[PDB]
Length: 134
Image (tube, rainbow, N blue to C red; front, side, top):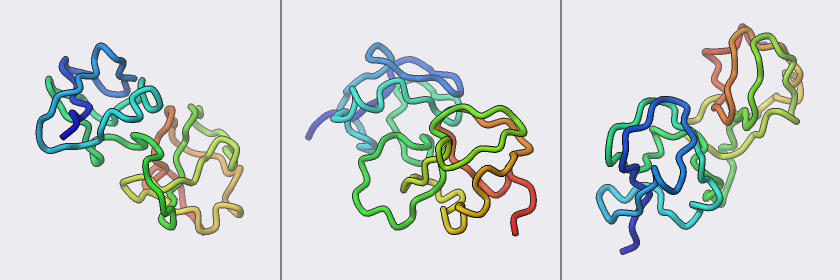
């Protein structure tokens, strides 16, 4: 089988991995492959990554758009938004990503709403970081 993207060195939290920190080794479990290496390269993680850590879906927010059928498109801040910032669909990208944070059900109504917490780059928007919805 093809090798997967397993980090050889240890990565801290929120760190874009590169070709040097990305090792294509054939280890299990076969998390995300390296076909989109040149696409999701520099992808930051949600928590600290140990040595030889394979790319996991639950450990990485939007590892890449390798999904086909959306349906469960979740809102993800592909960019960085400072606390209290009326973010709209432009800064928010409702795509199918895990885990299922906040689905774009009525986003058109909450779009441009000011957040009470700071938001980093591609981060999964959750109802725990926002105030009281409608």
